[PDB]
Length: 272
Ligand SMILES: [Zn+2]
Image (cartoon, rainbow, N blue to C red; front, side, top):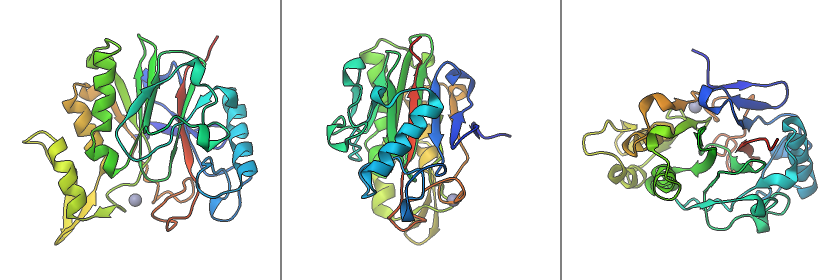
């Protein structure tokens, strides 16, 4: 059946899961920008060595398609850890045009205010979108193998539960386009770091393909952690799109051999 992320009029995929209908949520594709060479053309990342003018114009292009001004975006450092920070209108603009002013040392953000667009960069790692429609909360986390080993997904649920007094049953999640087991192979150190994060009897999100080599499914790993954290199975939507496989739409750190652009994952609510 249809992927939860479907292409819109311009260069971006909207999250089609029902629980997200009340927000502006999606992932950009690589087309429609000003960037050149390995970054062609809609590179949204300011920290990958691309021309800054080109990247800021690409972000202005998206702000235009979304009718959500760049001055209202909030970005974070993305250090491949599991920390998350709550943001408000007072953080608007952080890391929007200058990477150095991004929220430091975290890999996830959440807000319960409208008019704030959470914006994170990806090119293979897992983008995890969160929403509590009733309470008006939205969240976004960046999960590579290190952040997943650190439990970033469950940490978001924990924070919403303990600090925002939201029940896991009131949370919905969408796991967007990322590299699949079809293209992502890792060794024992990687999978060993994930083991402790899953329930004792849980099915493993990997498959040994050769002695010491594993086809890893990070999307599934995060899905299992979210289930354990209390998020209902039917509230979790998962994209089947692989960033490495779908070269016509995405930049891929692995497929492009380390030098490439970044798509922007975003989520926010329009301020009347
Ligand atoms: Zn693939």
